[PDB]
Length: 339
Ligand SMILES: [Mn+2]
Image (cartoon, rainbow, N blue to C red; front, side, top):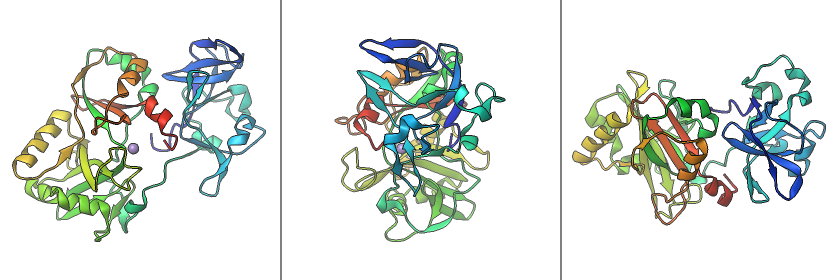
């Protein structure tokens, strides 16, 4: 899920009427709920579902319903899809019937049609503080930080009932990776490896908590992955003075896998024992899964690291390290229109 699966062929679920608003109804699409024109689908119908964060280029033939939300973004004219609320009812995504896409009459349920519809991914601007000097590509020997949304995991949420999960708070900052491979120690943003300058915010955070020394102490090819947050980083939800790093993952570069949560929270223990103050994203009570997606979304709303603000949401990592997912707070998305 990195620019991929924004537009997929999916199936209408339960179609509920909107009391008082007769021209439209609410369509369940997997874990999503979506406002449609009345009678546009019956339950069981297939259509293309365009997730929130889809950027769709203007076309009043195909996308007239998006006409008066066209904008300029990367010098591209088109409509960003985002969370909205229609008459007390949450609405996320666009769900159009297959008869609208002639080119897709061969395709099958669940096909990713993003590429072939030319759909791109809207994202917030990267923070002005954090565009440093690029050294290299994000190393290909490290995975980027990424979770599938719970809304897209109905059969897997079923399958996993009874399984236990590390539950962690999702922080609104910027992805940062600090790693060792042999004689090299590097620091990465989301997409790129960075040069150490005096102005580099990520390199500064890594020096300060001594996580570089940490990796020199551990003597392993590891990537420390987490969130840089604070002042002048994405509106500073947590109301920090200055800035800081909070780990949420460690990637084993030799074995080419993440460390399970217990593997991970032990290593952090020893770092803090040897004088390496590496902070971890807030960890909550472990979860035994026996929930709907809808229930998981409800538990995502809650307090953040700063417990006086509403959090971005939660991440769930099965304790064997072989299944993880995120649930973004819909309350958060309602309050935060740049999200
Ligand atoms: Mn984020």
